[PDB]
Image (tube, rainbow, N blue to C red):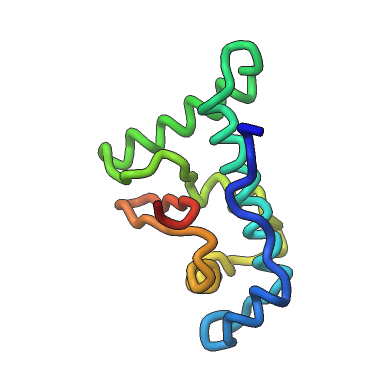
Length: 130
């Protein structure tokens, strides 16, 4: 298949690799929903990069406009092209999940599951590094 996941979910086998020194007030559940939602937005993105006008639907046009908006707002930065903004995943996670992302950043990278690029008033995230 062409459209395949980019980052699976993490269990106690992966979480156990991250001590409280990095988690602090986080938990497997918090990361499970973080890696799940992220993989979703990223999965659909890579799926469009290959799809065509045939599969391209309304949601495909809205995502392309927004995705290209942040990509062009980063000042032609970031060597990658498969990332998203926290403002797109945040409202996709959980309303009760609380602002743990900023704390999970070190927990997600400690395993090499995702990445984070600080570019001005924005924050991108790509699947590890090529």
